Image (spheres, rainbow, N blue to C red):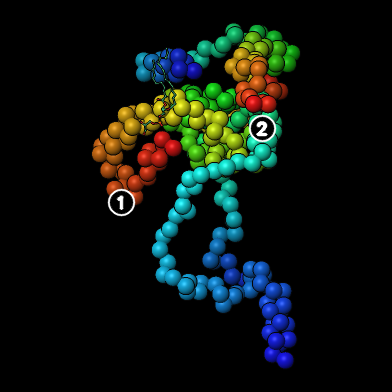
Amino acid sequence: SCCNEQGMRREALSGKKPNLWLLGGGPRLVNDSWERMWWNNLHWKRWKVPRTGPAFPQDMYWQ
Amino acid sequence: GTQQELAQMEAMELATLFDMSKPHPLDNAAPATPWKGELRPVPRKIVLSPYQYEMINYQRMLMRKNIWYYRDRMNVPRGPCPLHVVKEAWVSGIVDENTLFWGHGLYDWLPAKNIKLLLPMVRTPEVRFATWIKRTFSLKPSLNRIREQRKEHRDPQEASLQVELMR
Amino acid sequence: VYLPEGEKSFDITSMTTTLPFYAGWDESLKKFVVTNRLLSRRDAGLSV
């Protein structure tokens, strides 16, 4: 997010339409369904909770 | 004679005492002592019973896997927040005890200090030291500078949120 | 119905729009701006 913000600011100040770089990849040229077209970015975003949060319990029980 | 009449009148008053639409003569009455702005005395000695210990342990068991959410000034939910993300946001001065949070065990959005066990989890000694440093050396001088630079911040009406960030 | 309503505004709670913001090219102001105008739900998912 920080890198995209800085890049878009720099591109806008330079006189061009800014672009957004997606984590996972770009779109697929298909004509069936919207999920398949943007499968890579959706696949990256669907792992948000497992990627960040720990598997073990955060607090302590029984003590 | 008079006792029975007084008892009946008191029963009638009890009948409509909590009818908030009915005005009552004891409303806005003169207190026994002149009114002065007081504050609740801070407790000193606290002795917890085993009942409270076990209740706290049970509540910690229920909330040990929670993921929290909070709301910003524009009334938009903000980010999937595990415990360490909440701690980092608290240290950075983005959220405080008045922010609206939601977790698994609640039905509505409540202020952070009104959730049962959310402040003890965040406030580790390192978090306290870091938030004190951030409040004292980064946010306060910046607030002073922005107040001095722009006149749109009216001097008579100035917020005091930075002063109480450490808590 | 001949009842007073000037002391209040009939709204116990203010109605606030809840829409997340994002940055993009307006193409009308020709400026890079932050807004909250999303595509209508009558066309979301059907076509691109």
| Host chain of mark 1 | B
Q: Amino acid at mark 2?
A: Asn
- B11 above or below C48? below
Residue A48 seen by the camera: no
Instruction: Measuring from the top left, give residue B164's x and y in whole percent.
Output: 40, 40
Report how many numbered discs are placed on residues in the image. Answer: 2
* Residue under numbered circle 1: B156
Depth check: give the residue in front, C33 or B55. Answer: B55
Q: Amino acid at mark 1?
A: Pro
Residue B118 seen by the camera: yes
For the residues carrying marks 1 and 2, which lies nearer the camera in this image?
Answer: 2
Disc 2 element: helix
Q: Quadrant of the C terminus of chain B?
A: top left
Q: Quadrant of residue B126?
A: top left
Say the numbered circle drawn on residue B57. Answer: 2
Residue under the image location 29 percent in, 48 percent down: B155
Depth check: give the residue in front, B66 or B42. Answer: B42
**Residue extending farthest bottom:** B1
- A43 above or below B57? above
In whole angstroms, how far apart are the C-alphas of marks 1 and 2?
Answer: 47 Å
Mark 1, residues whose alpha carbon is within 10 Å: few (<14), some, or many (≥20)? few
Depth check: give the residue in front, B5 or B158. Answer: B5
Residue under the image location 41 percent in, 60 percent down: B37
Depth check: give the residue in front, B125 or B91. Answer: B125
- C37 above or below B48? above
